[PDB]
Each structure stands twice: as C-alpha cells, then as structure tokens.
Image (cartoon, coloured by chain):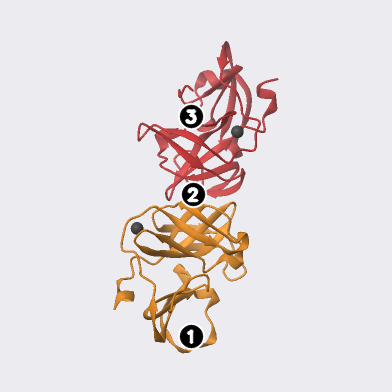
Chain colours: A orange, B red
Amino acid sequence: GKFGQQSGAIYVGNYRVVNRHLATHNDWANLVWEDSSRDLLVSSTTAQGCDTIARCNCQTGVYYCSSKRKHYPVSFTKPSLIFVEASEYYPARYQSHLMLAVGHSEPGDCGGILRCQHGVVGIVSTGGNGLVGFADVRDLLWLDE
Amino acid sequence: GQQSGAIYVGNYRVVNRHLATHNDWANLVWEDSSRDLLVSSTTAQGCDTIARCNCQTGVYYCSSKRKHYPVSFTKPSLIFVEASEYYPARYQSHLMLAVGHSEPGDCGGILRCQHGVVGIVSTGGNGLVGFADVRDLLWLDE
Ligand SMILES: [Zn+2]
Ligand SMILES: [Zn+2]
C-alpha cells in the first residue's frame, strides 16, 4: 500500500492522479497540477504511493473496465489531440494526450488503469462509439520526483 | 483475397467514392457521399463474397506498410471525421474504427473476416483506421 488498483486513481510517490472531472474537494484543496485539456488532476498525499509509471512507447497493454467487471488486452494509439464529443462533464472539444482503443467505456469506467509490462500507462478518460480513450501519463516525469 | 483497391462481387465494383474513376461514374449503380462509397457495374464477374455476419474482428491490408494486420473494430456508426483532400470536416456514416496505420493511399484496402468482405479502408488519422461497412448492402449479392 498504497496501490491505485480499481479505486480510480494512480498513487505514485506523494502524488494522487485522478480524472480532473472526478477530483474531490480535498483534491482541489491539495492541488499540485491540473489540465482540463488532458482531463487530469494531481494532488498531494501524505502516504507514499506504490504505482510505477511506465516511461516506454508501448502501444499494447491491459485496462480494467469496471462496467464489464473485466480486464481487457488492447492495442492503443499514440497520444494525440483528438476531438471528443460532449459528456456530462465537458462540452464537445479537443482533448490532448489522449490514446484510443477499441473497447467498452461507460462514464463509470473513468479512472480505470491502463498498464503495460513497464508500469502504468494512463487512465480511462473517454468513451463511446465502441472506443475507450485513455489520458496518457507517461510524459509527466515529475511524478517520479 | 485480392487487394486492388476495390471489391468485386458479381457484376459490381465497390470503391471509395472519392477514388472513383471517370469510368466508374459512367457506370454508376449507387453512390453515397456520407458513406464514401460508390458502386459501378462491371463486365466480368467478381470473386469476392460479402460478409453478412456480426464479426467485430478481422484482417485488413495496409498498402503503405505492405502488410496485413489483425484488428478488432467498432460496430458501424456516425463518426466525426476531420477534413481531408476530398471532404470537408463532417460526420461520416456507417464507419467502423480500429487502431492501425491508414494513410491516404491505403484507402481501398479490404477488411475481411472468415465470412467474407466486411468493408474498405476509408479514413485515417490519430492512429486510427476507418472502414466503410459494406455488410448492410444486401443487393450486392442479389
Ligand atoms: Zn511499456
Ligand atoms: Zn464474419
């Protein structure tokens, strides 16, 4: 402990990484960094997190889909700037650093973790039209403080 | 299992509408701009079989990589597509998506499953390959 698991967050060092749209009041009071275009928010924690962030260029991995109660292996795109249709939390807009795969994603699946052999790749962010999008974390080097 | 850039079934040739030739247009059977599809008549009989199934996995040919790739793909739907040389930004109908290489020259590559031809490469960008679904056009084998 502490591991993110299915909790909807990544815990690395003194940081907690969540979907920005799911961030709690405490997250915001504890804010480190947040970017709406990436749907990401990072808060500071007292306890030390055990998740390892992948530094690689893997395009294949496995994510947890809560709505199906299953892990799925997926091929996914490199992170890019992609138009995303409106959700409950965002208008139709361009989202940055987003990776897409074919898979099931309901709003409740957000926060599901995508992993490869090297560590945590990203978290479920978007869904619909039979695609699941993941916000990439691999470029944020400062998470490894 | 041919890849010529077109599907040949019976007396029909199925091609991307944006790649259709003058001869295709002089031979026109049906075309739909929102689907990026055009069908023309042919003199010679084609050997392709159109899949009637529900399959969401298959194999497509990517000309730019000179490779066939196994892919899982979405059910056909109405999808926003960024502007290309041939179309303005718009919603394209009956489009199925997978993760894969798709360049403009890859249009016409055929997606197949064990049952037959599923669709043809239509779109690409941000690391996705889109395929225009042909499985609903029943009249192709009628
Ligand atoms: Zn990796
Ligand atoms: Zn099939």
- Give neighbour class at mark 2: few <14, some 14-19, many 20+ (Cα, 10 Å): some
From this view, report whether residue B17 is shown above or below residue A57.
above
Q: Position of residue A86 (x, y in %)?
A: 59, 63
From this view, report whether residue B27 is shown above or below residue A108.
above
Q: Residue sitting at 58 percent across and 59 percent down?
A: A105
On the rendered image, what quadrant is the C terminus of chain B found in? top right
Which element carries disc 3, helix, strand or loop?
A: helix
Left or right of residue B75, residue A49 in this image: left
Task: Give the number of the mark in front: 2 or 1.
Answer: 1
Q: Position of residue B15 (x, y in %)?
A: 53, 27
**Labels 2 and 1 in the same subunit:** no
**Labels 1 and 3 in the same subunit:** no
Which element carries disc 2, helix, strand or loop?
A: loop
Q: Position of residue A24 (x, y in %)?
A: 54, 83
Tell me the quarter of the picture where residue A50 sits: bottom left
Measured in 3D between alpha carbons, the distance from the residue under mark 2 to the one under mark 1, in whole angstroms, is 35 Å
From this view, report whether residue B48 is shown above or below residue A114.
above
Of callouts 3 and 2, which one flags the residue occurring earlier in the amino acid sequence? 3
- Give neighbour class at mark 1: few <14, some 14-19, many 20+ (Cα, 10 Å): some
Q: Residue sitting at 42 percent across and 40 percent down?
A: B102
In the rendered image, the residue lying farthest to the top is: B43
Proximity of marks 2 and 1: CB atoms separated by less than 8 Å: no
Task: Give the number of the mark in front: 1 or 3.
Answer: 1
Which element carries disc 1, helix, strand or loop?
A: helix
Would you name the residue on which mark 1 appears? A28
Identified by mark 1, the residue type is Trp
Q: Residue sitting at 53 percent across and 45 percent down?
A: B97
- Give neighbour class at mark 3: few <14, some 14-19, many 20+ (Cα, 10 Å): some
Q: Of the numbered discs in the image, which one, if any, rests on residue B19?
A: 3
Identified by mark 3, the residue type is Leu
Proximity of marks 3 and 2: CB atoms separated by less than 8 Å: no
Nearer-the-camera pick, A28 or B36: A28
